[PDB]
Amino acid sequence: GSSGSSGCCLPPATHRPHPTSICDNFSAYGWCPLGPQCPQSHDISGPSSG
Ligand SMILES: [Zn+2]
Image (cartoon, rainbow, N blue to C red; front, top):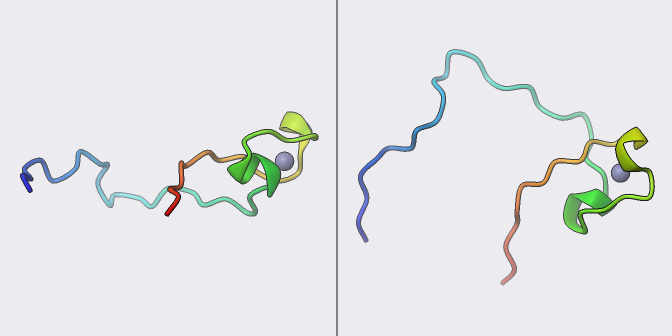
């Protein structure tokens, strides 16, 4: 297929900070019974099925 722009992502100047541990509920489900207080991080990436 067509392809031009080589992704408008930030330079390698510095690698972004990585999480310590993602939750199990908010991870996929999206919601968590602990809310923001939850000790685990809640990062919504957006996986695919299939
Ligand atoms: Zn959680």
